[PDB]
Image (tube, rainbow, N blue to C red):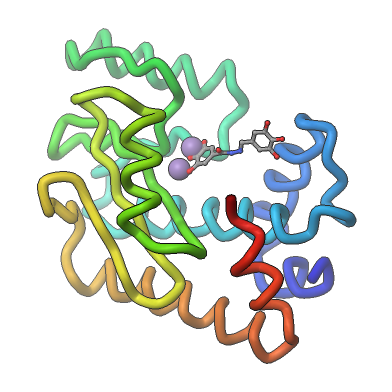
Length: 177
Ligand SMILES: O=C(N/N=C/c1cc(O)c(O)c(O)c1)c1cc(O)c(O)c(O)c1
Ligand SMILES: [Mn+2]
Ligand SMILES: [Mn+2]
């Protein structure tokens, strides 16, 4: 699985994921499923940010915490939007709202609900993807066009297929709590 992550995700994603894990005192070489999940989430966030017009999205995920909150507080002051309690993943300049992105190995509806409980904010939009082509977004509002969304769902299915081929998928699918 460590070989898999290092060959399927670009080095910038891998580096961010290793750092996030070490910040919690986890070793990427041991908790390899968490490692893979962090990388996949990061890639989806970056893919989503590329899905719109140039300048449609500001990326918040993948930033150190000081810069992430600088970006968030800046947007709240520039736009007057409510300040979230937790860092979201992106801000949408077209829709004027923060987005929380979820990627789940279980079922989208359960993950949407968990996310909606934790976020517990009216303001933040939630968009969940599975590795088997399912998605679920706030007010059935999917933000991006179908072509962009299909390219994300396809990348996730491809990662699922690659893990499967290495007999990694079963352990990975079962590691999400
Ligand atoms: O919950 C998330 N990450 N991990 C939290 C976490 C908390 C712990 O106490 C651990 O021991 C751990 O391994 C991970 C998580 C999930 C997302 O979709 C995000 O966008 C995000 O910023 C964080
Ligand atoms: Mn995030
Ligand atoms: Mn997220």
